[PDB]
Amino acid sequence: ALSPTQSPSEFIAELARCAQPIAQANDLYASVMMAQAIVESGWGASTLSKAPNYNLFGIKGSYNGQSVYMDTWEYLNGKWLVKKEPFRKYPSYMESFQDNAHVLKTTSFQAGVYYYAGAWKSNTSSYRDATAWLTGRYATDPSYNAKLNNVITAYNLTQYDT
Image 1 (cartoon, rainbow, N blue to C red):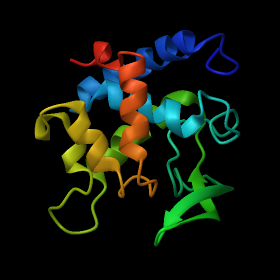
Image 2: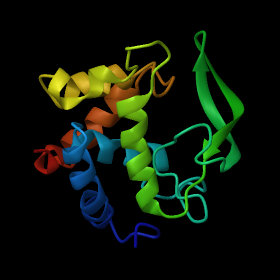
Image 3: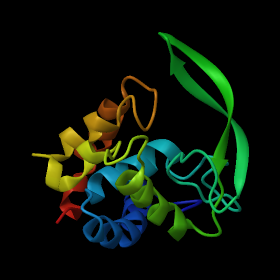
Image 4: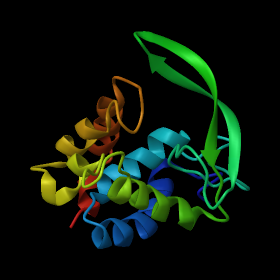
């Protein structure tokens, strides 16, 4: 299953079935989507990513009012700190994929400016531009793009892009 899974190969094949169509429909890289699920969830092992939360993507805030508070590492002003933060809670694994796409496509702090626009496939030359854009935006980890890129390259995840 996504959890527990027999191998990275299993986990990847199961992610692709959801990620490929959603990424294609939304001008996103499937590879980046799948890397974010692997890195955020720890191959589907995190409590946040498992039932009854199903949040594969470390998405913060609330989903139709549904949230779970969890301890999380943040990198702030040059220090790693544990913070307790609100994460979205979903009814199944599918909504977390849809919501990752929604967050990337629609997040805006200023009129006419989409915060994640640099991770949209049409605004990039390669997936590396998208992972770089997420760093310091989606997550505070200053090595976030290196962690995503390392998963993409190790597992040839651009095979799922189109």
